Image (cartoon, rainbow, N blue to C red):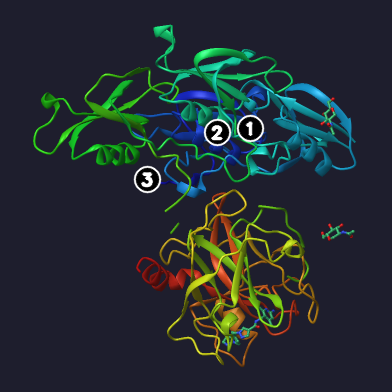
Amino acid sequence: GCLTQLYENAFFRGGDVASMYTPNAQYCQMRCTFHPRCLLFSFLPASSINDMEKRFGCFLKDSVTGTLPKVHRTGAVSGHSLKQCGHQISACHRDIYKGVDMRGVNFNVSKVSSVEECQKRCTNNIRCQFFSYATNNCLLKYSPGGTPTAIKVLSNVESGFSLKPCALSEIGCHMNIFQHLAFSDVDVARVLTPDAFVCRTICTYHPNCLFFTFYTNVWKIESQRNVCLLKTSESGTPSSSTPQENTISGYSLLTCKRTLPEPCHSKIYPGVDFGGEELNVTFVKGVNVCQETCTKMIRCQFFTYSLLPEDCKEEKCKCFLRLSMDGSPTRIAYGTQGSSGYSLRLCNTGDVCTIVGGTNSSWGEWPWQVSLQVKLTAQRHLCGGSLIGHQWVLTAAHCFDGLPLQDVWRIYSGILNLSDITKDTPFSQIKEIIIHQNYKVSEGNHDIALIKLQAPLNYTEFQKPICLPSKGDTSTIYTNCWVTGWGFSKEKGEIQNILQKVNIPLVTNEECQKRYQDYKITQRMVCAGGKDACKGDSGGPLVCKHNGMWRLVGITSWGEGCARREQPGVYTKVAEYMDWILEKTQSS
Ligand SMILES: Cc1cc(N)nc(C)c1CNC(=O)c1cnn(Cc2ccc(Cn3cccn3)cc2)c1
């Protein structure tokens, strides 16, 4: 099961399967998440340890129990992989580190006006993995495994990673595969795959893979059948291509914006066995059950469901759960009674999960944010909203006051600049509106409504759901809460074109009551406050970053003016409507 909690001042003892340098702990957790064996990680900031070569140190760990001895160590951050965490799994990491120099193979040097300009050049260079900017020349870099070979504290250097895996690369996306055609170049790794697309997906998430050649099982040389060769080159593109019977080549799809493959392989393969280390064997009823059994057991990486009469009892046959060192079968045999497949633990396309005084946001920064517009005499943006599921958006009830809740509404998602919206821009239409039963147009109670879209949305890195809060467990005092929208930047201002963001401290429910003596601030409301949500931000998100994670805490509802001194914003408190949410939303 998904496990997002972190452990402060804590180091896990032993169990190392890999280690590298990473700029912070969440980056290390992402490495853990994508490593085939990592369940647990411990990270050491520059302050925590005094062994120079351990600083910025990221240690990836496995354990047959799923647990390891935990030792106290001031400043060390331990935690879990995000395997099994669905759409919270993400290869994208846009943080820029001030005062930090991440080192590697410097292969390209330029002069640019800002760190941002440097990040962009890295992002658009097929070979760039991370970069460093000084203060103004710009260094693009790669390294073994994509992590820096060293990380040093230098006050006037900023560093960050290519935003390629955030879908921001202008580099092309190449969906073409080439039949009977082999690449040469630099082989960076070699694994067995059942077909070419699995191999292409492994290439896409492999740090140093830019293209691949796969060898089918009809391949002349028997010992090389099903070999998937991950490759790269200095230029980043193949320098030759050789015609070759029974040979399939293609490219990493990491630059692809809307065809980025999921980092799991969900096809079932009849007549094939996947060899590996045996982890557990049990009698389940059919291949699908066997695959779920593998997905729920986190150390399982792939399986074979046997169909030999000797391996079946009554409707139930042996389900061989297996793993290997690198996540791929150690053998693939093609004449067997039964079917093989992979664990879905890393699938991230989901099933729902558990502005005055701000600055420009960046594309995909807030991927759950939507704009709710109305086609009346003109089309206009009225409210924000939060994507919480393929078909579901959460917003404010008052957005529909006296409004013809029919074929008038158009929901926009995955969008940063409203001015970019033309009548050809794709949009979601409303299939159904769920205003809270106890809502009333002239009162602020239960300011919340669901919207079922007429079609489900595909999750991308610029369009995906925010997670909701766990139970009524808001005893936790959130410290890093933010609010976004295209609303008025001042009282009596205008709608903004570029989605805005602001960091607002939360307030107490009694202190908030003290400042609105004319209304009743209730338990089901949460308050927060020269910086505020304003007109047109209605219904948008109030998000809090907990354990490096983002939670949806409030729905922008109301305030007296905008950004008025000691009159804070009132948000519908999401914790207190989970019952109704999950209710209306897990049905129909
Ligand atoms: C105007 C505004 C300024 C601001 N700082 N921020 C926002 C987002 C807005 C936009 N808001 C609305 O346009 C609006 C209209 N109607 N509603 C529902 C509602 C809720 C609460 C009350 C008063 N109340 C508080 C507790 C009990 N009652 C009255 C109306 C919202």
Q: Reading the chain from its start, which is encountered first: label 1 or label 2?
A: 1
Whole-percent x, y for residue 254 in the image: 61, 35
Residue hosting label 1:
22
Q: Nearer the viewer, residue 26 or 337?
A: 337
Pinpoint residue 209: horizontal percent, then vertical percent: 60, 24
Q: How busy is the neighbourhood of tag 3: few (under 14 within 10 Å), some, or many (20 plus)?
A: few
Of labels 1 and 2, the one closer to you: 2
**Residue 191 or residue 355, whichever sits in front:** 191
Q: Is residue 197 above or below residue 3?
A: above
Q: Which numbered disc covers residue 289?
A: none
Cα–Cα gap, marks 1 and 3: 26 Å
Looking at the rendered structure, the kind of residue marked 2 is Arg
> Sequence-wise, which precedes: disc 3 or disc 2?
3
Can you say which quadrant of the picture contains the C terminus? bottom left
Mark 3 is on which residue type?
A: Gly
**Residue visible at 83% across and 35% down?**
133
Q: Which residue is mark 2?
A: 31
